[PDB]
Image (cartoon, rainbow over all chains, first blue to last red; front, side, top):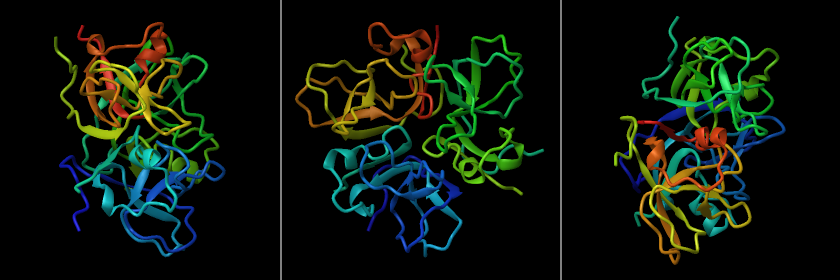
Length: 103
Length: 103
Length: 103
């Protein structure tokens, strides 16, 4: 049940939430360009996951807390269904986040 | 007059500047895609602010210094006029920068 | 032969590789949007270099290791031929990476 796969500090940040339904912790997040808010990462593009949710949401919150850095265990993250294995590997590329198999 | 709202190290970087007028410190920056240079963040998109200016510019400089990490106090940053509250909250999402209300 | 130009920790990450030919260490990387894999940064856009290769590749590897943070010496990096001086200066803007002249 280990969440990290590396020792680099895992810093958190807050942001405006566009999530409108319950969402578990360790969900990757992306920006919604129409609103500028953070929503669940849809898996469509590598590099567009900009955060990993820290606290579960109920879907009513205007703000959320996310990890903006750290190295996560791949298996701990709640990935979107259907995600492409390469886009999953490189979900966070370009941010300070990364992930790796423990395994 | 506190500039930071968190303890994560605030690292700086240098970059090529496209700014041609005086600009105060703690201004968010974006890339200009036509030139590749750093300019003032226009507020149009969340996640496109890639830096926060460290030293004031006069507008003649070919290079600038910017913060590439850290957690800033929202009120300390010199935001662009008109900015959308959500795009402002998520200005830096995807970078190692973030900001929060002290308040 | 110094590779770093600053003291901020240089963290590494792994990612899915789309590189199919030998590639030296300290090569900047970008995402290929069609596949989601990491490939050599082509120099076309500032901010699209998301990593710097840590280990040389032979071109057969499905995964690679890259730096996701740190301040590099400009001269140590293996830049793409033809790169624009401004796009080169700002190659990594928006990531936790940066570079500077030692010189």
